[PDB]
Picture 1: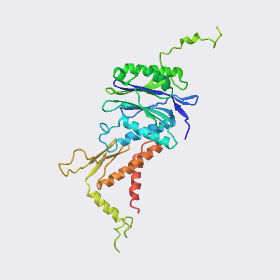
Picture 2: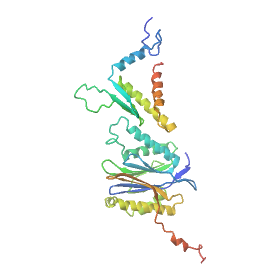
Picture 3: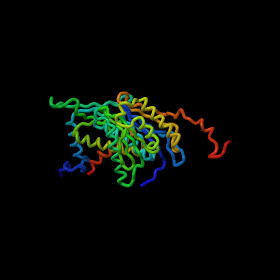
Length: 233
Length: 122
């Protein structure tokens, strides 16, 4: 039983016609202190899988190296680690899920919320979520923290049911994610302007964009806001 | 008298360990394998005896990888060689886990060396 120290806010993501997108800002907060601005919280495993982690950052780093060990060990005595017996998004998920529920069951959680995103070998999109309780679920859109409350409603306006997915393009998908990241920056007090975004497409493979900034913000109307009621100047 | 070669950790009267020397005979009965150290790396090659046409090519892999940067190959009793690699793997993980840097080759050599030596002690 612990309490988180250095933290990362929302991870948000959805799936479109050909694959998935997942985004996360580059910040580790220390309570109210915005302490670290270089934090990469999207962990790519292979080239069919990105793993976005929110929650305690020491526990994330631990999980992060578990993933490397998992790639090293897969490739032991395996002449097919670069095809057919390469790591699959669902394998990486079931493992994490297993560890999460086990740590919860030991009363010593890995204080995180994880979203596993990628494309399976057959071509199917993978998108699933596990958290520090070992609770798991899938939806065409997924998000942790504030993202759950503010990002999901925006994203569900694009992909509101499974039948909407083959209709949604990468441009449309990528659009939504970026707007959502901006809304989060407007309204989440533990968030950051700088963020990373990854697209895993069944035909373009893994595309990983670092050092993105929130752009196109509306702030102008702030000049007209005076007082909190009766003040005119 | 006689019988110095029956138990593993016994010094013969000339100071030798016959069980080790017998093990060496099992190596010699093995297929041949080599390593060539070049100017920026190492090559490993091995002889795979094709007993029959029933074998599958090239589906009986003998060379093993430890961590991500170490190749191992061995001659002799094969299951013994896998057991040793297994131990090398745990050892290299344990090293990375604590020290972050992947195990340097001499460090790694000593890891197997101390462990092989250990089996000539009891």
